[PDB]
Image (cartoon, rainbow, N blue to C red; front, side, top):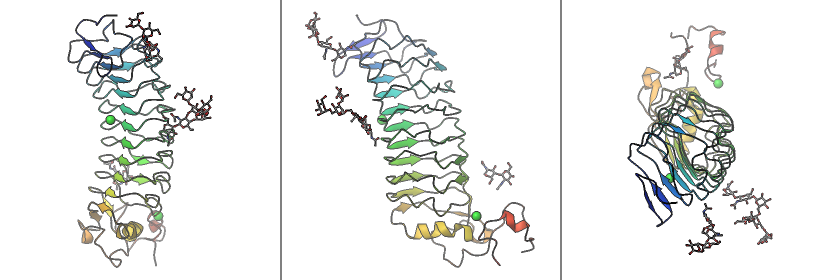
Length: 310
Ligand SMILES: *[C@@H]1O[C@H](CO)[C@@H](O[C@@H]2O[C@H](CO)[C@@H](O[C@@H]3O[C@H](CO[C@H]4O[C@H](CO[C@H]5O[C@H](CO)[C@@H](O)[C@H](O)[C@@H]5O)[C@@H](O)[C@H](O[C@H]5O[C@H](CO)[C@@H](O)[C@H](O)[C@@H]5O)[C@@H]4O)[C@@H](O)[C@H](O)[C@@H]3O)[C@H](O)[C@H]2NC(C)=O)[C@H](O)[C@H]1NC(C)=O
Ligand SMILES: *[C@@H]1O[C@H](CO)[C@@H](O[C@@H]2O[C@H](CO)[C@@H](O[C@@H]3O[C@H](CO)[C@@H](O)[C@H](O[C@H]4O[C@H](CO)[C@@H](O)[C@H](O)[C@@H]4O)[C@@H]3O)[C@H](O)[C@H]2NC(C)=O)[C@H](O)[C@H]1NC(C)=O
Ligand SMILES: *[C@@H]1O[C@H](CO)[C@@H](O[C@@H]2O[C@H](CO)[C@@H](O)[C@H](O)[C@H]2NC(C)=O)[C@H](O)[C@H]1NC(C)=O
Ligand SMILES: [Cl-]
Ligand SMILES: [Cl-]
């Protein structure tokens, strides 16, 4: 089959059908089945039917970023067993992706879902993608991080989740990520992290948690991070008292580079780095919940265990 209109087809280095920066409001008909690389970025494609791309059995790279995508059929990528790169980024209209869209893509190693406005990550959305190494989910509308979302992503090295409305980190949210190298979770709403949440992140070297809503960090949370060399806890409402003691001992016994850990409370130790603080500064308590040692024994029950010291 000859090359379709408003397109350029060539064979070197791979059989490529290139139709970018056109006025195409949909996928052009007549794309050669021999295509290994398809470039349809910079257009105005609204929908991606299931019939399209099926002919291209040998398709390895597919670019559909910077379009007007709003609805992708669940069987659109059926038959593309050799698909390696899939870029669907910069599609703010694409608010939701059907959980069975990526089934069968066992060769996919890079996936772009950034700047799409994804509200949620559907159950089984990343099931069976055991070859995925780069997953871009940054700058979406994600406001939840469900357990076992990346359970099958054992080869994943880069996971970008920054720029979302993610409120907390459940225990099994990052389970299965044994080969994770960099984890970017900055500019979210993270205020709570489970003690055994980084259970499998032993090979993690980079962890970005800055610009969040964290007030404290448990004792067992940073324990499994044996390979961590870069850590950033900038821009967080840290509370510097007895509850910050397990974090302080960790920051002290840490060789890798880490950003500043600015205190927010109490005002006495405000703006100072928890790193440089001494063991004496980490006693008593600071104001939490209702603003105010005139608290009753019942009232201090709503305070940390160390904070309840007599
Ligand atoms: C990152 O992703 C990796 C994949 O991208 C993943 O690697 C996968 O690991 C899993 C382990 O859970 C493997 O699953 C296993 O698959 C094998 C398949 O058989 C394998 O070994 C046979 C050996 O055959 C022998 O006998 C034949 C005679 O028939 C001889 O010729 C041969 O020389 C041997 O003596 C081999 O033939 C298989 O080859 C496959 O691929 C060729 C194409 O190259 C096909 O033509 C062939 O038919 C066959 O399908 C294959 O190597 C299975 O038997 C086990 O039970 C188990 O299910 C995956 O295969 C493996 N995928 C790879 C390597 O691509 C990594 O695990 C992942 N990383 C992390 C951390 O999760
Ligand atoms: C995806 O990739 C696979 C694997 O690379 C590929 O299967 C292969 O297709 C090519 C070409 O279609 C095959 O090579 C040809 O073999 C046929 C017979 O098998 C020959 O007829 C060809 O020789 C000439 O004849 C043609 C006209 O009769 C000429 O037009 C042509 O230019 C040649 O001069 C040619 O050598 C190859 O045998 C298979 N199999 C393998 C294992 O490579 C498949 O086609 C690709 N595309 C899709 C959609 O699957
Ligand atoms: C950061 O987290 C705090 C909770 O620690 C959020 O504020 C709380 O809001 C609830 C009501 O939903 C109150 O009961 C709490 O007393 C509030 N706590 C504090 C410390 O204000 C706050 O909204 C979060 N901020 C962001 C930007 O997500
Ligand atoms: Cl990449
Ligand atoms: Cl506590």
